[PDB]
Image: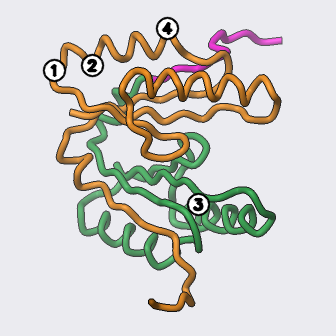
Chain colours: A green, B orange
Amino acid sequence: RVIVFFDLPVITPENRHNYSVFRKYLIKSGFIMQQKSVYSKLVLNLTNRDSIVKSIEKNKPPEGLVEVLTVTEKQYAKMEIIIGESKTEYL
Amino acid sequence: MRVIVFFDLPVITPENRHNYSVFRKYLIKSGFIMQQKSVYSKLVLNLTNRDSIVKSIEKNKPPEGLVEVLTVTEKQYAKMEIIIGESKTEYLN
């Protein structure tokens, strides 16, 4: 499991445009949102992983930081989830 | 090992922004290193301490937002790929 998390400027309209362009690129590459600015994708082997990361490099935004972490599916399923308004209640 | 905290907190209102700084401060106080605006990490030398860290984050959680806590090896953390934004048509020094 490949995790892409990024820290991009959001001050200007052009910053925000550039943010949306990079997000759409990730979506277009099969990445799913885990939370804001954090996306993940299962990969079958490390060749596929390296190729994903190379494509991120070629499509990176003009400013900001993008980091790529690779973990096992077990490590990912053991992630602790903490939600502020935690209760589940229907109307 | 390393504990990575990914947080997605609202910043729409003044209360949201205050609570954002409170949580970030709690992470600093706790010895987490900022990695990105919304991603902090801490070296863990003893797996016993991991469960203690998670319980503390749970007790100190902000009133709204998503906090996800991932445990990875030192090697996975050291080999993270760091990609720096750059224009496709940047001038070179």
Residue ID for mark 2: B50
Element under disc 1: loop
Is residue A39 toward the left or the right of residue A10 in the image?
Answer: left
Q: Main secondary structure of the magenta part?
A: loop
Element under disc 3: helix
Residue ID for mark 4: B59
Image height of A91 relative to A71, above or below = above
Q: CA distance from mark 2 to mark 4?
A: 14 Å
Q: Is residue A70 magenta?
A: no
Q: Nearer the viewer, residue B14 or A85?
A: B14
Q: Residue at x 29, y 45 (%)?
A: A71
Classify the position of the C terminus of chain A by image quarter: top right
| Type of amino acid under label 1 | Asn
Is residue A44 toward the left or the right of residue A81 in the image?
Answer: left
Residue ID for mark 1: B46
Q: Are marks 3 and 4 in contact (CB under 8 Å)?
A: no
Mark earlier in primary sequence (4, 1): 1
| Type of amino acid under label 4 | Lys
